[PDB]
Image (tube, rainbow over all chains, first blue to last red; front, side, top):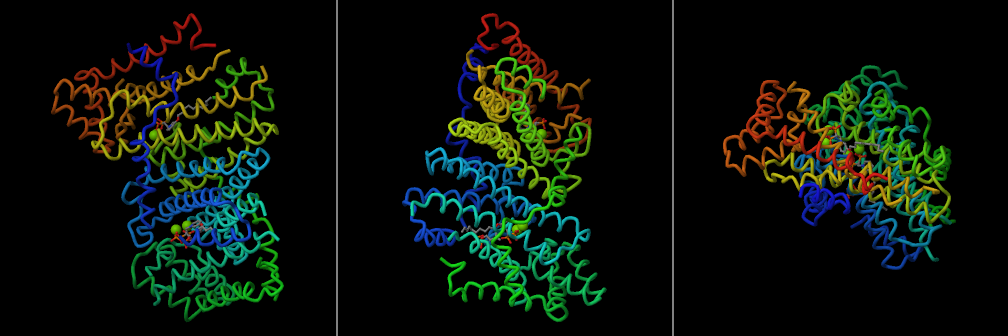
Length: 299
Length: 298
Ligand SMILES: CCCCCCCCCCOc1ccc[n+](CC(P(=O)(O)O)P(=O)(O)O)c1
Ligand SMILES: CCCCCCCCCCOc1ccc[n+](CC(P(=O)(O)O)P(=O)(O)O)c1
Ligand SMILES: C=C(C)CCOP(=O)(O)OP(=O)(O)O
Ligand SMILES: [Mg+2]
Ligand SMILES: [Mg+2]
Ligand SMILES: [Mg+2]
Ligand SMILES: [Mg+2]
C-alpha cells in the first residue's frame, strides 16, 4: 500500500492546495495593506492604448515586482518600517519573506505569458522582463556593495547615477517597454529613465529633509545616498579631511541615535550644502521636462 | 547646459555596467562555486541533445542550483556548506540574497541560447517558470512549518508533497528541458520524482545518522522525514511527554551536541524513526532496483 501511494504521487503533478497558497502569501499580503504606480500606467496608455484586459495584467505584473522588491529591499536594508507599518520580515521572519517575494517574482513572470499568444511578441515581452530584472539587480547589488564595503569605494555622482539607471530605472523601463511592445497604436524610455532618476534622488532627498523638519533611516542604513555622495566628494575636494572622516564615521555607526543622525544632517547643511545642492539638482532635472517645448522627451 | 547634455546622454543610453561591477557583485556566487554533471550525462544517453545544447542545459541547472543553496543557507541560518563558511556570513545576507536572485535571472537569460524555434522557446521558458514556482512553493512550506512550529505538525503525506515541490522542482526542471530538447520512450518524470524523494529523505536521514555514529537539521528546527514520523508516531501512541520534548528541542535552535544527541536517541529507541526512515528509503530504492517491466526506468 506504501508502494501504491508513492506510485500515485510520482505520477501526478506536485500537490499544492489553496490553503498552501495562503500560507506562502502572508508576507506579501501584509505589504499590500499599503495606486500611483497605476496612475502613471493609466496615463501612459493614452498613448499606447492597450485594451483594458491587457493593461490590467501589465498592472498586476508591475504590482508584484514592485511589492516583492520592497519586501526584499527591507530585509537588505534592515528596515523596521515600511509605509508607516512594521516590515514583513519582522513579522513572518526573514526566511519566509525572502521565499515569498522570490515566489512572486516568478508569479509575475507567469503573468507575462498571458499578455499575448503571438510567438514573436511573447519572446519580446520575456526578453524585456528578463533584461530589466537583471538591471534592477545590478543596481541593487552595487548600491548594497558600496554600502557594505564602505569605506572601500566612495562613488562619484556619475557612478551613483549609473547605479540609479539600473536599480530604479529597471522597473520604470520594464513597465514602459512592455506597454510600447503591446501597443497596437518617439519612445518614452529616455523620459521614464529621467523620471526614475528624479524619483530616486527625491526619495534620498526626502529621507533627510523629513527628519530635519522622517526617521532619516538612510543614515542608520549607511546608504551612499545622493546628498551623502555629494557631501563626501565635496569634503574630499575641499580638503575638509575631518568632515570627510566624520561623515564616514557616522555612516559606519549604523546608528539609530536621533542626536548623531542630526549631527550628520547639520554637516550636510552648514558645511557641504548637500541638501540645498540636491534640491537644486532635482529642480534642474525637472526643468528639463518643464522646458521641453519641442517635446523631445515628452510625448 | 553641460550637465543637461550629460543627463540627456545618460537617459538615452542603456544603463552602464562594467565587467568590474560584474565581479564585485558576483562574490557570494563565486564563493560557493569553490566546492550533477553525471546525472545529466547518463540521462542524455536517452535524450541525445548535441553537446553544445547539453552544456547550456548544464550551466542553467548549475546557476539555479547554486543560487538555491545560497538562499537556502540564509533561510536555514546555516553556518557551513560543503565544509566551508556560507557566503552570507562572509559577504552578508544583503549581497548574498541579491546575488543569488541575480543568478536566477541569468539562468533564465540562458534559456534563449537553447533554440531559435519560437514554439519550443515558449515551452522551455514555461518549464523553467513552472519548476521554479514549484521549488518556491515547497521551500515556502518547509520554512513555514519550521518557523511557526507547532502551529502545524505535518503528516508523512504532507511532507512528501512538500518534497515533490521543493526537491522535485530542479530534478524535473532539468529533465523536462531535456525531454523537450530531444531530437530522438515514456516520460522519465515519475522516475525523476522518485529520485528527488529518495535524495531528500536520504539527506534528512544522513544529517542525523552521521552524527549519531553536526545534525545541523536539529539546530535549524526542520520538520525532517525522521522528525515528522516521530511527531506523528508520538501523538498516535499517546507519548505526550516525548511529543512535547521533540518540539521543545526543535524550538531551542540548539547547537549543544548532547541535546542534539538526546533527540537522535529518542528517534533511535523511543520512536524507531531512524529505522523507519532507513527502511522507507530502502523500499523506495527497491521500487527502482526491482522495476523489471521498466515502468519507472527507461
Ligand atoms: C511606472 C511604474 C512605477 C512602479 C512603482 C514605483 C517603482 C519604484 C522602483 C524603485 O526600485 C527600487 C529598487 C531598489 C530599492 N528600492 C527601495 C528604495 P526605498 O527603501 O528608499 O523605498 P531604496 O532602499 O533603494 O532607497 C526601490
Ligand atoms: C539533474 C539535477 C541536478 C541538480 C540536482 C539537485 C539535487 C538537490 C535539489 C535540492 O533542492 C533543494 C531545495 C531547497 C533546499 N535545498 C537545500 C537542502 P540542504 O541545506 O539539506 O542541502 P534542504 O535545506 O532542503 O535540506 C535543496
Ligand atoms: C522604493 C522606492 C525607491 C520608490 C518606490 O515607489 P514609492 O516608494 O514612491 O511608492 P510605494 O513605496 O508607497 O509603493
Ligand atoms: Mg530600502
Ligand atoms: Mg535599498
Ligand atoms: Mg538547508
Ligand atoms: Mg532548507
